[PDB]
Amino acid sequence: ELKMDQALLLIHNELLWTNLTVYWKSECCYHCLFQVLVNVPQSPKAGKPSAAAASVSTQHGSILQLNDTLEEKEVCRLEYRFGEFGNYSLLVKNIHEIACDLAVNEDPVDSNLPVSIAFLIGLAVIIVISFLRLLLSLDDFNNWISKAIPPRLRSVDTFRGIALILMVFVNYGGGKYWYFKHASWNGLTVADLVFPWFVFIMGSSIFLSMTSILQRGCSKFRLLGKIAWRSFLLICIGIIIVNPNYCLGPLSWDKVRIPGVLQRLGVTYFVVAVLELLFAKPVPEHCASERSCLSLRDITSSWPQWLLILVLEGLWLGLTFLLPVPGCPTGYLGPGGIGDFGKYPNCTGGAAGYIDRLLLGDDHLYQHPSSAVLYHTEVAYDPEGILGTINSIVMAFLGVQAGKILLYYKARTKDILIRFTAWCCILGLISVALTKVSENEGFIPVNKNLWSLSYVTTLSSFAFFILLVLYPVVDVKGLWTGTPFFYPGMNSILVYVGHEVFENYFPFQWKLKDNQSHKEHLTQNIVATALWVLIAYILYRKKIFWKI
Amino acid sequence: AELKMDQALLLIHNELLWTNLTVYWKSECCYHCLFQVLVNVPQSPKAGKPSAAAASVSTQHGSILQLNDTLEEKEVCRLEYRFGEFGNYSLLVKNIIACDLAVNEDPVDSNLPVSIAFLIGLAVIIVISFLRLLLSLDDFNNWISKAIPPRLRSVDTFRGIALILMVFVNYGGGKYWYFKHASWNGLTVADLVFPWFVFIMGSSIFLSMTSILQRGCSKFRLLGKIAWRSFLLICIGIIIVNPNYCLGPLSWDKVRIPGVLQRLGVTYFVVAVLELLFAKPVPESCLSLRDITSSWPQWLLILVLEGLWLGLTFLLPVPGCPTGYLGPGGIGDFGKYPNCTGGAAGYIDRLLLGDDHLYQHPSSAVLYHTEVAYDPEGILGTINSIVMAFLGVQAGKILLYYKARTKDILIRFTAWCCILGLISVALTKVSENEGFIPVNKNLWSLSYVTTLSSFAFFILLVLYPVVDVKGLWTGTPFFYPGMNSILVYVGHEVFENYFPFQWKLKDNQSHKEHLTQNIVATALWVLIAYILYRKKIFWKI
Ligand SMILES: CC(=O)SCCNC(=O)CCNC(=O)[C@H](O)C(C)(C)COP(=O)(O)OP(=O)(O)OC[C@H]1O[C@@H](n2cnc3c(N)ncnc32)[C@H](O)[C@@H]1OP(=O)(O)O
Ligand SMILES: CC(=O)SCCNC(=O)CCNC(=O)[C@H](O)C(C)(C)COP(=O)(O)OP(=O)(O)OC[C@H]1O[C@@H](n2cnc3c(N)ncnc32)[C@H](O)[C@@H]1OP(=O)(O)O
Ligand SMILES: *[C@@H]1O[C@H](CO)[C@@H](O[C@@H]2O[C@H](CO)[C@@H](O)[C@H](O)[C@H]2NC(C)=O)[C@H](O)[C@H]1NC(C)=O
Ligand SMILES: *[C@@H]1O[C@H](CO)[C@@H](O)[C@H](O)[C@H]1NC(C)=O
Ligand SMILES: *[C@@H]1O[C@H](CO)[C@@H](O)[C@H](O)[C@H]1NC(C)=O
Ligand SMILES: *[C@@H]1O[C@H](CO)[C@@H](O)[C@H](O)[C@H]1NC(C)=O
Ligand SMILES: *[C@@H]1O[C@H](CO)[C@@H](O)[C@H](O)[C@H]1NC(C)=O
Ligand SMILES: *[C@@H]1O[C@H](CO)[C@@H](O)[C@H](O)[C@H]1NC(C)=O
């Protein structure tokens, strides 16, 4: 009857001489049009109101505006938040103006109230018990037959493993929860964090591997060849394997999505690694005093790259806020569709979307952006577009900066911690200035689809804080080893390609008894993520590390 | 036009007034099929204006048309014609009743120009493109620099031939009928790879077992390795290879338990454990026959297993079905056994695994219109798969016992090939549908096993001197997949739909485009195997 995250709204219209139409919009919309929910006829006679049934969305908030069909006047307005499976009744009547009362016939399922952390810890206990029993069964079976007859940081690795586990969880569905999906246009969800963290970690590893290779006595040209080959392979693997849905049919060139996650990673890797190789200064030595020296030797040594990154960021800001888009406001950052009151429907992405549609074409972009379900956008927008690559490069260079911090001051963790704290604080201040700590307001609101500058600064401050926490615990104090996380940290590309390839396979996806149940989807996605962690751990035990 | 691939437009118009015509169709290859209706041709309203009809007749191989008056059910005429692909034929029936079937436009051969010189042209194109890709990329790098126990290889070649053929026929084989699995009885090019794979698996079982045991390894560690490999093969087949995940998520009550890799694992376990249990060191000749008497317990057990297969096939009473039924069911055998596909083997696997846990689209479903699910890699045929794996083990025994006696190996290979060919001739009477046990991949018939074993022994007889002794030709396109068989199979199952192997065609009703796509995909899989060989990334177990 009712789908997932969808209540039932019964609308009894007791008025005699007024047609009734009901409009609905979410509270997550910034400026959305009022979609038609249902049209309720007038009551044929007193005491027998006419009723119409509507299925309202539950995920986040709801606004109801009831208007007459004849005169189009506001009868009454509602801002109720509905439950996942409810039988709400909306009675409109003339008590005198007209007073409408909303009644909850059946109480909500109250999603996230029942599962809480109790269900999650129970599922973890169950899977741990099953894994232990499976491990112990091998010994009993064997006995029965026998009776008859530089080193890796591991903080970067734990960070990458956290990102990979979260990415596998949110990519497989994340329980089909709205906060485990990418945000529609603006704001930040759990699924919007992993990709910037992946780019940040990629930049950090770029600096780490490049400086290790250069200090081992390697030529710059061979390293450039390796960088070019890796970027080319990333782009090709993305385009051929990761982007297309091969269950829909054979891959035609006219409908090939050129941009993608791996294409963005390859392009940014090439750009920032080539910048690092062009300006590659050896890691110098400190004063060996530990007396709060606070030397800015890890920024002035890279001012080449800082100047070029600032030029690229200025280019991104100019192309975003200044490039004229035909039939579209200059400097448009909205989602289009019904967003911004539906006056710019074919404007999803503004300048970034325009540049993507111009250079690559509509057919070669992402056909189903995140805004399509909330703002009802019809144009194809690619989150990993062309303008966003500039900010992807900027964040990869911030990750390179983190690697420079943790390599220049490798001797003392005090300097590393202060550098990480200062960078996190500065990036957080920049993000607060840009977005005014607001989801949809601010100069540049946080936006994964546009890869906003505030998106980059917010997620970079998050990654710097994550490093500030993980580096002492995992490395200096050694209190933790990233115990379940670092195996994906070592087999990141294998995990990504595998879960993009084996997404529909049985251990990661099976048929559920109820597909509208959040609990079943969450159980399946958690099991699949745990199985990918298990696969990464098994490969780690076998010393198998696929590297490009 | 509206003509699908392998179809001809048949325009039937009758210049007659006082009879209604219904046209029946029956492909020539089917053994005993009911005449399925094709089209109903009504009376012409008046003389001089025949009433026309349209029908798309299959042109894969032959066609028999039964035109009988639907009012009285008497055949006005019956003609057997080999229609051409994309043809346009006018079956004119009128009083003199005479049927002629004139030709309106010429058909398309679809096989001669596509495989006479098109194959050479495509091979030239692919080798030129590969050379250009390998050279131009390296040309830029060279220009920039200026500015700045051993494997036999005949078994490997045989396995690579089987893998190339399997990749070609699984991907479609150009959608040609002779590159698909035969509808029930008979042999096609696609019906040879799996028995060859089982034969090679048995030969490799013996070679690996002898090497491991002569190296001093214990029998229990080897038994654990056997069990682990069989379990892994079964699990891979069940989880990765069998399901079509493009349809939807996997449910237990709709999962195909049998399969290619499951059967390979079961036969590997049985044959390898038999060899390990009755394991003897190879001794150290013109007329010795020692490699047959040494494995007399295994031969006795294989004879008992074959007798059990014969007894279950020809004596097990299947309810609602004739005993010893080797036919395909459906409209085959005059449609008197509509649900009898496989007979005893189908009954056994339906009773033990259920209709849901079988292959829901048997190869006979298109020709004989069978409605039951029959699994070619079922339960009863696993006995014959074990037998053919043991024949492969015998080939490995021949290879290893007479290692230094090439003439002895050749004599043994030709003797086994001739003996198994004689058995196949006796069982089939050289006939696809006649004989005591006709050749059948779906049933994995005993004569199927013996025919493919004689073929494999002849292949080995031709390959052993050339690739090993005389060194005339290493399996230079073939051993590269031969040493990565499991990777090639699993990858081509997983990446079947991916771009290098599949892309959207200009028209899917074209044998030329499909053949080009499948040959390109097979060549790309050979190239992937060669790349893995060059980097030594042989995946095993
Ligand atoms: C939005 C969603 O929900 S889905 C979006 C998902 N986004 C993604 O980016 C997922 C896919 N991406 C990835 O998996 C990764 O970003 C990758 C594989 C592309 C890049 O991984 P990277 O972080 O660049 O590191 P990778 O493991 O490939 O190794 C690169 C180099 O860094 C080195 N390195 C890695 N970790 C460390 C470490 N902790 N310390 C030192 N060196 C390290 C490696 O040794 C290697 O150098 P080498 O080749 O000279 O030996
Ligand atoms: C019907 C259709 O169109 S599709 C159906 C066809 N598909 C199939 O049959 C599935 C694909 N099959 C296969 O890939 C293979 O048959 C397999 C991998 C499943 C079977 O493995 P095998 O054929 O025995 O070969 P594999 O390469 O795995 O060799 C296994 C052992 O034999 C040894 N071996 C293999 N070839 C040789 C050789 N030429 N000389 C010596 N030893 C050899 C290996 O060393 C290994 O022993 P080890 O563990 O001691 O090292
Ligand atoms: C529902 O009715 C209200 C009230 O009549 C509408 O809001 C006002 O009226 C016009 C449209 O008639 C709006 O454009 C104005 O912005 C509102 N204020 C004033 C002062 O007019 C509302 O637009 C109606 N909703 C729909 C979907 O028709
Ligand atoms: C209400 O809607 C009905 C449509 O069924 C229409 O016939 C009627 O005239 C409407 N009444 C008013 C007051 O608009
Ligand atoms: C909702 O409640 C009304 C009365 O309270 C009842 O008639 C109706 O069947 C209920 N609907 C559902 C889906 O439970
Ligand atoms: C042939 O069929 C047509 C319509 O189906 C019918 O009108 C006619 O009477 C039939 N002729 C004979 C001889 O049955
Ligand atoms: C067509 O009619 C003839 C008349 O003898 C009959 O023998 C034949 O079986 C018919 N074809 C069918 C029923 O398919
Ligand atoms: C087949 O030939 C006839 C000749 O009368 C013609 O009318 C018909 O259009 C042809 N069919 C096609 C598909 O061209």
Image (cartoon, coloured by chain):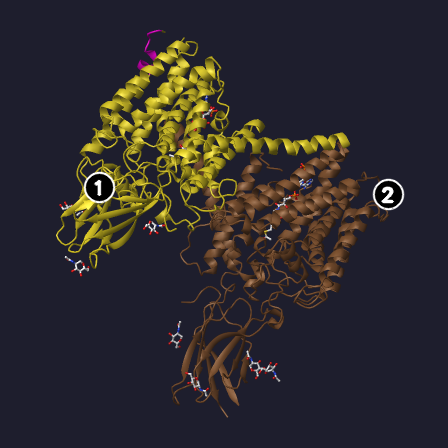
Chain colours: A brown, B yellow
**Callout 1 secondary element:** strand
Mark 1–mark 2 Cα distance, whole angstroms, equals 104 Å
Q: Nearer the viewer, residue B256 or A371?
A: A371
Residue A490 in the figure: left or right of residue B217:
right
Residue B107, position in %: x, y? 35, 41
What chain letter is assigned to the residue under label 1? B
The quarter of the rendered structure image containing the N terminus of chain A is bottom left
Is there a contact, CB below 8 Å, between mark 1 and mark 2? Answer: no
> In this rendering, does residue A150 appear at all?
no
Q: Amino acid at mark 2?
A: Ser
Q: Nearer the viewer, residue A143 or A184?
A: A184
Residue A359 in the figure: left or right of residue B390:
right
| Picture residue at 63% right of the left edge, 61% below the top | A188
**Disc sitting over residue A499 in the figure:** none
Same chain assignment for discs 1 and 2: no
Residue A291, position in %: x, y? 86, 47
**Callout 2 secondary element:** loop
Q: Which residues are magenta?
A: B286-294
Q: Quadrant of residue B238?
A: top left
Q: Which residue is mark 2?
A: A289
- Residue at the limit of the structure toward the top, as seen here: B286
- Residue at the limit of the structure toward the front, as seen here: B48
Q: Is residue A183 highlighted in magenta?
A: no
Q: Residues within 10 Å of mark 1 (few under 14, many from 20)?
A: few
Examine the rendered structure and indicate whether residue A454 appears above or below residue A73: above
What chain letter is assigned to the residue under label 2? A
Examine the rendered structure and indicate whether residue B35 appears above or below residue B133: below
Q: Amino acid at mark 1?
A: Leu
Q: Residues within 10 Å of mark 2 (few under 14, many from 20)?
A: few
Q: Which residue is mark 1?
A: B79
